[PDB]
Length: 150
Image 1: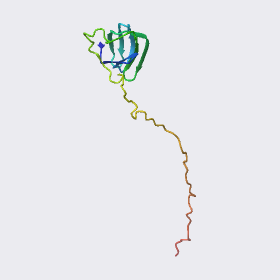
Image 2: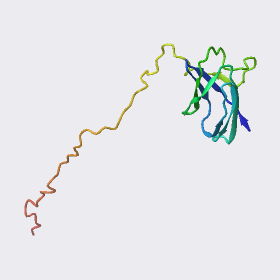
Image 3: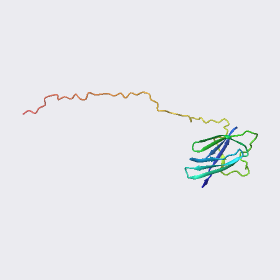
Image 4: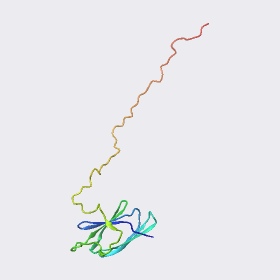
């Protein structure tokens, strides 16, 4: 009925990233407070529901919100830089078992992600020739009067 796969978190100075393992997104209704709220999604690839709840120890700015999805739904929300948010989860005593860490949206301390990844090729046109030769057809002639004599 209700599903909760892995949900990866990662943060930057201003914004925070939410990496949800969700192939086919359907009817996503998001209730988030700067202090915590619950989000409801529907999984179209299974026919199942998705539902998680986030209690925020830190404080969020629900104004800046982006949902970008490849094979998964990445939801980036801007954190309100009020003072010091040591933890994202208000309930640090008991985290949700579906909460995990995103190893790719973490603050890259001098990494590099352009490692021969940007290789593009096109079907460019160059020379159109299609030159062909033509023959006369035939020059075969009966050489001699080859007849059967008696």
